[PDB]
Image (tube, rainbow over all chains, first blue to last red; front, side, top):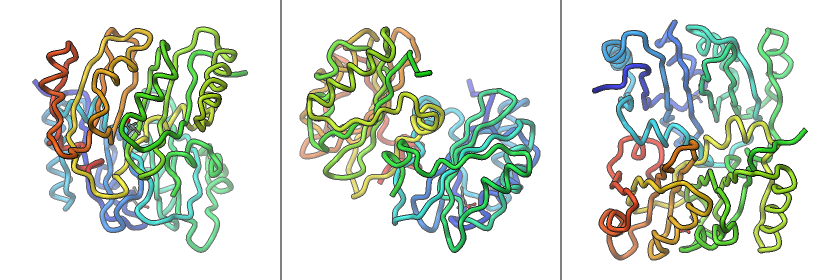
Length: 182
Length: 182
Ligand SMILES: CC[C@H](C)[C@H](N)C(=O)O
Ligand SMILES: CC[C@H](C)[C@H](N)C(=O)O
């Protein structure tokens, strides 16, 4: 038998500004229900992606084909018991070189294409260095994301709240500092 | 208000063989329902620990006092929203230096002290370099753990199955290889 309710994918995307947005553009108007990443390698980022399905294995195959035809390396984890039980809860670590990060929590209304619309709303001026999101089937999705400071303080807590997305600065969070910062 | 159902703790323990077992000995006959770790720093390991409570904040305080009196550095994350929503699902990463690991899945019967009994049953001959466990309130707890090879192939799949703990070798798992191995 095969998992029918969701596609679980290990995707490599470029470790550069705007790469998450470009990848989600290809996913398009789908219900992307998980997206987990933390800066590790400076060239290739590793993302754990979950997509809710309505047409089961065939739809999983269509997504895999689309991503390959788009030039992405993807490993299908949909039938992988350790991915389903453990590894989707283990995307983290400290970065391979020291980062100067700002951490924020956000909420976005859930519907097909919502993660894509949220990533576009953030924009690509700052590099995303951490992302954690899992849908709970609720009306709003809850995201944790960090951004590299670069040359200007990220503006998310002003701009995103002006645009109808809840946003809070979490940079001094003790759990982030203990397990993830570096 | 305060969280009453569980204590969530960020604990530093020595990065050495037998350290997890020694820490869980101090926790004793408690319902340890989460224990997440991945080798990072070679001196100090960082563990995310959850303990189910029956006496709420007072019991949380008793656990914190006991751990401090035992000489452990602990940060209380029980009321930390980002820990509860995100970071407990983000304990992972690749190790700070390359490791030669063997990965196994296990199941143990859930009851007070069960994680302690499982860690003692494993023994301390091999260093644990990865641990993921979250209780789902079910009769059996499901663990993912990796061990450094050292000088002898770990014996868990023979010995632990002889002792009434289910154990399977997962060393070639694609999700581990993609997100955690290093
Ligand atoms: C997942 C984030 C990716 C890799 C990239 N850093 C970005 O800012 O889009
Ligand atoms: C969590 C594992 C700890 C740090 C240690 N490596 C052990 O084998 O007990």
